[PDB]
Every structure is written in C-alpha cells, then in structure tokens.
Image 1 (cartoon, rainbow, N blue to C red):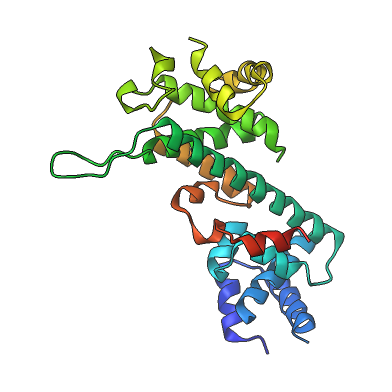
Image 2 (tube, rainbow, N blue to C red):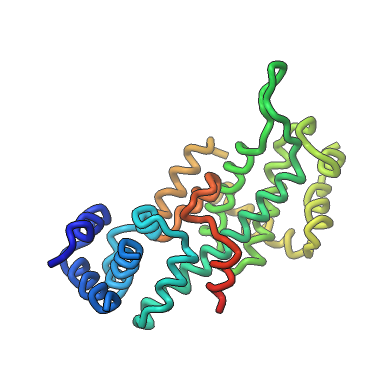
Length: 259
C-alpha cells in the first residue's frame, strides 16, 4: 500500500526498511504537495530513529525544496522535541551561512575589479577568489568554531589573507592603496565597522592555527570540505557558489520562518 513513487524516493535516499515504514505511517497521519511532504516525513522518521542515511542537501535535491520552505512545512506538523531541535539547528546553520556568504559576495564586489570578456581580453571576475576564500573559510569555521559575529571576524581574516596574495592591478580602491603591512585588515574593519582588536585576536588564535595546524589548490580544499559535509549530513555549503536553488530563499519564505 506504499505508493511506488514513495518507494522510489526512499530507494534514492538509501532509506532502511524501518525508517521507510515509519515515514509512510507519518505520511498517512499528515495526509489525513505530496513529494515534498514525503521528504519531510522521511526526515522526521530518520531523525526520530537516529538513522540518517542521506544528507539534508541530498534530501532537498530529491524533493526540490529550499531550506526555508522545508522549515515552514515541517513546523506545521506535530513532531518530537528531537525533530524540532534538529530542524532548528539546521535552520540556524543555514541562516548563518547564508548571511556570511551574502557578506562575502558583497565584499568581493568592493575589493575586486570586474570586466566582461571581449575580443581584446578575457572576462575578469571574482569566481576564483570567491570559491577559494569561501571553501577556506568553510574549513576554518568548522575547525576552530553557528554564532555569526565571531564567524564574520574569521571571514575577514580569510579575506585579509587572499587580498595579500592578490595582484594590485585587480584591486579596487581603497584596497589597491592598502597594498602599496597591517594596512589591509584596517581597511576591511574601517569598512565593515569591526573591532580591530577582536579581529586580530581571532586572526591569531583561530585563523593562524588553521592555515598550518591543518594553500593546497582549490580542488583539494573542496574534497576535504566534502568529507566533513558527508560526515555531518547537513548542507553542502559549496552550493552557495552556484546559487543552488536548494539554498536560495525569497523574502516571504524567510519572514515566515521567523514567525
């Protein structure tokens, strides 16, 4: 009496039999859009039974839903405290990451010149720096670190590092001037209105362990992040770089998530 499309979804997610059964019973309860609700029931069952055979991103890609919409759907279902906590934790992880990534994207736009490609020249964009600094930041955050403010000060340390390795001909003002010493970190702070001392502290006892007590090429760094993501079974934060639908929101969904 399971729908075949439900059975197939469970197969894609490697769901063991007891989890699949519990998820279906959950659906029958809630059942008193189908595929999204099924994914939610699978998540509820997997969390309640301590048997997660998939990552949250994987589940999302299968049912084609954003984090916020998932949250707003789930919150309307009576669930256990365990489930409530799991979902709240994921929501916070996502909101922190989304906030930090938005900031990274905006800051890069202020640091680096942009130029469309033409007959005379190749396109100049910050895709390479975005990718490497984001992944490097992702690795650093999980190493020596949720909690947005300290995370952001750490992101500035990562930004400082990559600015220093950057060609000045690719820098916008005032960053170009700042590379003609402790100058860059000051520019960043005097732009984002941060406590320089606290950022310095994070630099020393957070950032600086990480970069040795741990630059390989990007693909290597990506592979290391992937191992940690697969282990934690939450979100593949690299997908932010692709503006993956699973990680996009709209203003209305976001607002509802807080209500």
